[PDB]
Image (spheres, helix red, strand yellow):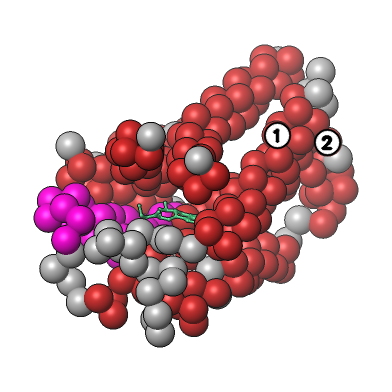
């Protein structure tokens, strides 16, 4: 079951890589931010998920060297954060595009896309900047009874608040403002509302339980909490596996590209 998620991740990300890099009609500023998101989930699907499957297969005892535990957790907080701020920036851009379309089109450029990519990756690197320089030289953030689990309450609580919950409330405000703003064109607006709702509720359903139970594991019968964490982390990874699909399949050109490249 676990091996299915890794394969789905690599395939669904390589498909959008090939669809944006080898299709003239889809070379746009928005498709390049989607390209960056796909790159983030692509790296997450190879540098993290195989190692997580290895940990599940072996158990808590980890055959890889203890020195390597610090950087493998650093990649999780790097790539998963990067994807989360990618989604947050996409929602903000959609709100600017739907609420004020003339001005968005006036300000739309490739420079804005590069600025967005630089900003989200800078923020992701900054949030995960404590862990390697505080974890390689000690056991504070890297180890807890031979589990290779992030065991720093100062960073688990504070880190999640900036990495997930600030983006989460930004996304909820953005969704409520957009759906309050889209109220032949009427059917298009209804389909846009449908897509926005589906995407937002997928992201919330798939990432919210992990961080809630992670906070509860620190504030708070922890044996069941450990297993729930161990399942919801994989749910979170499956979200990054899915995200390239739902953000692109609705577009006709992307759907045709996936139909053709799969042949
Ligand atoms: C190494 C695997 N692992 C052990 C089960 C984890 O807990 C990993 C730790 C994580 C974490 C902790 C704190 C703040 C955070 N922000 C973001 Br985004 C993440 C995060 C991603 C999250 N990923 C999915 C699991």
Residue at left offset 87%, top offset 48%: 103
Residue at left offset 65%, top offset 42%: 168
Earlier-in-chain disc, 2 versus 1: 2
Q: Which residues are magenta?
A: 36-61
Task: Identify the image quadrant of residue 39.
Answer: bottom left
Q: Is mark 1 within 8 Å of ligand 1?
A: no
Task: Identify the image quadrant of residue 119.
Answer: bottom right
| Residue designated by label 2 | 99
Seen from the viewer's position, the closer of residues 256 and 207 is 207
80 over 237 or under it: above or below: below
Q: Is residue 59 left or right of residue 244?
A: left
Quadrant showing the N terminus: top left
The location of residue 225, given as percent across then percent down, is: 38, 37
134 over 63 or under it: above or below: below
The answer to if 261 sits in the magenta stretch is no
Give the prevailing secondary structure in the magenta stretch. Answer: helix
| Residue designated by label 1 | 172
Q: Which mark is residue 93?
A: none
């Amino acid at each position: 079951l676990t091996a299915v998620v890794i394969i789905l991740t690599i395939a669904g990300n390589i498909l959008v890589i090939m669809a944006v890099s080898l299709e003239k009609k889809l070379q746009n500023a928005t498709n390049y931010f989607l390209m960056s998101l796909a790159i983030a989930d692509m790296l997450l699907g190879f540098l993290v998920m195989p190692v997580s499957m290895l940990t599940i297969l072996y158990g808590y005892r980890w055959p890889l060297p203890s020195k390597l535990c610090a950087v493998w957790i650093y990649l999780d907080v790097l790539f998963s954060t990067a994807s989360i701020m990618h989604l947050c920036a996409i929602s903000l851009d959609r709100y600017v595009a739907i609420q004020n379309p003339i001005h968005h089109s006036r300000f739309n450029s490739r420079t804005k896309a590069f600025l967005k990519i630089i900003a989200v990756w800078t923020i992701s690197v900054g949030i995960s900047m404590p862990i390697p320089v505080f974890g390689l030289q000690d056991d504070s953030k890297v180890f807890k009874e031979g589990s290779c689990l992030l065991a720093d309450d100062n960073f688990v609580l504070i880190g999640s608040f900036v990495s997930f919950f600030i983006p989460l409330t930004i996304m909820v405000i953005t969704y409520f403002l957009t759906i309050k703003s889209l109220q032949q064109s009427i059917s298009n607006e209804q389909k846009a509302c449908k897509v926005l709702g589906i995407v937002f509720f997928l992201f919330v359903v798939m990432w919210c339980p992990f961080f809630i139970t992670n906070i509860m594991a620190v504030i708070c019968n922890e044996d069941v909490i450990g297993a729930l964490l161990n399942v919801f982390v994989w749910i979170g990874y499956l979200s990054s596996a899915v995200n390239p699909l739902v953000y692109t399949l609705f577009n006709k050109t992307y759907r045709s590209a996936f139909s053709r490249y799969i042949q």
